[PDB]
Image 1 (spheres, each protein chain N blue to C red):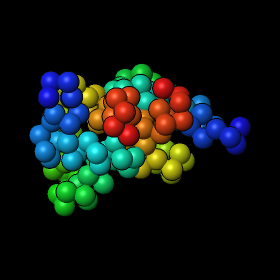
Image 2: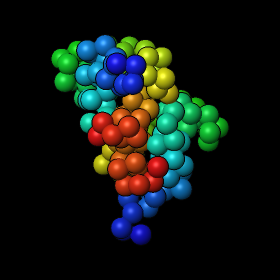
Image 3: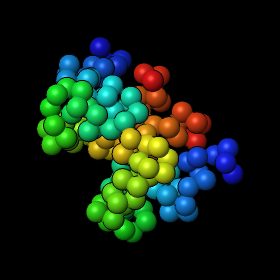
Image 4: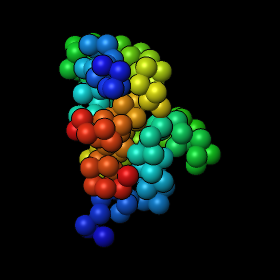
Length: 69
Length: 69
């Protein structure tokens, strides 16, 4: 639970991460969740707060750092 | 030379990567190169092509994947 950070996030936020950390971008996340590059960006900017991510770059970076991918 | 992909890039493009792969975002790249979020984004979107990066996410992701950070 509190051990995790990238997966302890909200279900969508976790989906967000996996789609960024995937190795594409927020646009692919939108494409994945069926949202929009506009919609997920609002989740990326908030993941900036939640995951202490810089904006998106850490969302994908920290995942590998942790061992997620 | 041809072995590298992330660092074989243009001097700026390499600087771009290191600032994304750093663990902040393109905005920190802008702030690092003293450009702008609007100018580096133009480099990120082209690094999409150069590095085969998905937009920016791979720029920071693939770095760790390779062992850059």
